[PDB]
Image: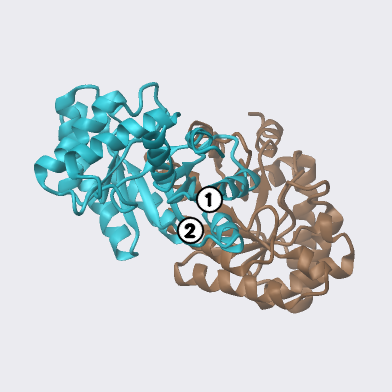
Chain colours: A brown, B cyan
């Protein structure tokens, strides 16, 4: 019953995603239908900005307007041009995004520049906050690699106003891992910002067994009631099929 | 010849150098920006999908051609009749930094008998663009409208709704720009007397210097040789550029 319990919980915390070079309106429409499962709705969908308008219409017409729409900006590169990252974020807001997952300029941080990351996140947060849009920040743990760098990127993002810190883009060699997730959640804990900052493991999370492990870390650090939609999301795709299977669907 | 060479340079400077492919990337757009800066002059603009505007702007600036405009497309290529969606995409295009937005008119709705939605859609998008000092071109998709009466009607509605340019096609259907469609649309501009405020843009399938010459000849005939400047005429094309340069000995 433990795996079934965690699987249903994980399903309801999913940011059902599709960020492929071959994405089409038709594929996103299908994703919206998938988000409305036989056992409940996912927390949201995560798609490229251009698909937001049609996705919003699709979710509304099937009676699931509560399924949030997240998107990505400064993605997947995480370049350090704040003007470009901000323009993309403002465009995402204009398209109608409920949430924007922006990529932190991690290569700049690896090069010893902590200021550009703070300013980039802050600028995007200011834009999102003014539009009642939540901002998640992707630090790309797989590329940062070192615990110190993962902690630093998390810390900077939090100080700059991140509403969520996310592990990866799903576009690099290594993405979410239990180890990286624990480090990032430890930062939220050490900074005492668990009430205002959520966590989102993303990329490579494909099985119900994996999801259970990620939620176990959250429960361990913040108590079993902490991981609600405002504080936890699963950036995944095929994971949904695995969760549904564990639930007999 | 001499006339052909002259029309080719003129057409080059009026080109909205385009790339709107499913396999487009930042790299391909950067290459497009480089192509827009030719040895005999710069194209009037580039036309790309909204998401590529920021990097395109940076690329044009770094190569010393900030005067090359950036046009994009919305409600594309479908021309659906949902005004909220068309408007949202247009506002996003503006936010990305577009100088011009080429929106697709709800042509199937018009064909089904709805003249009002086209007026309302263009008007809503024009309002957003004008508020940001962005020009709005309206694609009526002549290849699908097919009939002369429908082409004139879509052009008239678009103009009344505030179009800054009327454009023939998306380039995503079989039949796009044709000399006949261009003449019909320009005749509407002439008949309505809006040549000072409304430009024309033949788009799709315009591949040769010879073709470009014919399209410009129609404009010169109807409005005089000095009418077709960047604010009033553009070529929505891609491979055309190579043909124009070849005609010029480049």
Q: Give the quarter of the figure containing the C terminus of chain A.
A: top right
Task: Categorize mark 2 by other alpha carbons within 10 Å: few (<14), some (14-19), many (20+).
Answer: many
The numbered mark 1 sits on a residue in which chain? B
Residue at 44% across, 61% down: B95
Q: Earlier in the sequence, mark 2 or mark 1?
A: 1
**In the visual, does A89 lie left or right of B8?**
right
Where residue A245 appears, as percent x and y from the top left, is: 69, 31
Crowdedness near tag 1: few (<14), some (14–19) or many (≥20) residues, C-alpha within 10 Å: many
Look at the image and tell me whether residue A17 can be seen.
yes
Measured as percent of width and height from the top left, residue B118 is found at 21, 41
Q: Which residue is painted at 35% across and 59% down in the image?
A: B134
Q: Position of residue B84 (x, y in %)?
A: 32, 48
Judged left or right of residue A53, residue B220 is left
The residue carrying mark 2 is: B96
Residue A145 coordinates in the image, percent (x, y) = 87, 59
Residue that numbered label 1 is attached to: B51
Left or right: B78, with A239 as reference point = left
Residue at x 83% of width, y 70% of height: A111
Q: How many marks?
A: 2
- Give how far apart the Cα atoms at labels 2 and 1 are: 7 Å
Q: Residue furthest front?
A: B2
Callout 2 touching callout 1 (CB < 8 Å) = yes
Q: Quadrant of residue A219?
A: bottom right
| Mark 2 secondary-structure assignment | helix
- Looking at the picture, tell me which residue is in the foreground, A77 or B231: B231
Q: Dot 1: what SS?
A: helix
């Amino acid at each position: 019953t433990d795996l079934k319990a965690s699987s249903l919980r994980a399903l309801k915390l999913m940011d059902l995603t599709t960020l492929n070079d071959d994405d089409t309106d038709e594929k996103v429409i299908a994703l919206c239908h998938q988000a409305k499962t036989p056992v409940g709705n996912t927390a949201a969908i995560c798609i490229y900005p251009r698909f937001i308008p049609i996705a919003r219409k699709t979710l509304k017409e099937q009676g699931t307007p509560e399924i949030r729409i997240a998107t990505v900006t400064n993605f997947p590169h995480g370049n350090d041009d704040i003007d470009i990252a901000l323009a993309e974020t403002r465009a995402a807001i204009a398209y109608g995004a409920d949430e924007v997952d922006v990529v932190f300029p991690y290569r700049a941080l690896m090069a010893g520049n902590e200021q550009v990351g703070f300013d980039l996140v802050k600028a995007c947060k200011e834009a999102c906050a003014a539009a009642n849009v939540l901002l998640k920040v992707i630090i790309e743990t797989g590329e940062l690699k070192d615990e110190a760098l993962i902690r630093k990127a998390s810390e900077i993002s939090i100080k700059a106003g991140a509403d969520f810190i996310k592990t990866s883009t799903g576009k690099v060699a290594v993405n979410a891992t239990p180890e990286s997730a624990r480090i990032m959640m430890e930062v939220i804990r050490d900074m005492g910002v668990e009430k205002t900052v959520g966590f989102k493991p993303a990329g490579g999370v494909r099985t119900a067994e994996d999801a259970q492990k990620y939620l176990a870390i959250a429960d361990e650090l913040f108590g079993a009631d902490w991981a609600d939609a405002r504080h936890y999301r699963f950036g995944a795709s095929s994971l949904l099929a695995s969760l549904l299977k564990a639930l007999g669907h």
